[PDB]
Image (cartoon, rainbow over all chains, first blue to last red; front, side, top):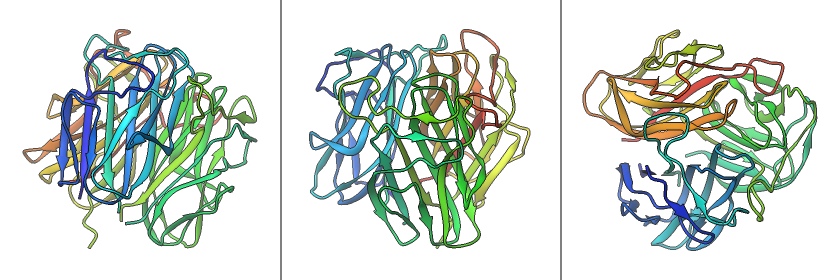
Length: 137
Length: 137
Length: 140
């Protein structure tokens, strides 16, 4: 079955309207999902239903939405109201044209530009942002 | 494959013992799982094992459990100790009678009734609560 | 027809976790298939089928903390997660490939600055919460 994991380990900055980049690829199965390391783009090449999860650790309160083909997905936006705490969201979407593109967009954090942290809680390097996604139809 | 995504976008209030309602259906596939918009009832019509995940953003610390037919699911209860911080949990469970109902119940938050926040961290509307569930066996 | 491998384990205690130690889970949830096993009271998820697994963990501690998923004693790439807020969930979803069997998945205090971490089974409410948990399934 189709599965993809991507994550970032950097203190990248994301401005309103831009996407989270992922510098590393985890395990990828199947051929429906792909992703070029260093980009925020996740290419989807099979119609049907997908379930995506996102985690993002920033130094400020933030608001981020999953976006499909540049448009926010219904139920795809999550925010945190506490600094230095996780922003996490799981949501499903239907791909009706291929290739589609899934991104994670700074959908208007109040603070404006958001800077991620790969250092929270410990002295070792964290995943600062990640998406885990699989097809369910 | 049986999958369901429902989510809410409101600042609803939830009393101790009441369920979180979901105003919006995301993708649902299969015959096992369903939900009527506006309710907090996810109805499960096929026996087997299910993996449910919930997310909830509230204006203060809270405690919620997934319940099945009115009974807390073992491992279905999660709390957070920070206002405007996400209460997220993932729990698997077995359905031995059908149809059965899955709810997300205020159970039992210290502050009493819990009001959600659909506006944390940004200027657009967030998912204030949601469930992602699929059948594994 | 239904050979999905799936396991859910969770803990309901205020366990103390020294730097380098693993989160233990006192309770087994549903387990399907043959690949995955866990002896309660341990933090060891044993994996006896080669392939690719997705592991999600949740952890509720009284201080900010940094934990990593580890396989056979080595931190998994993309498996380390930290939060900067006390009494705030540490939540991470990562996927890894098991290249030898048996392999042991653990979740380890991979050096929170505060040192020994103590979980909370009581945040938010008057009932007992899941203070730590892992849900894992096989995708490849």
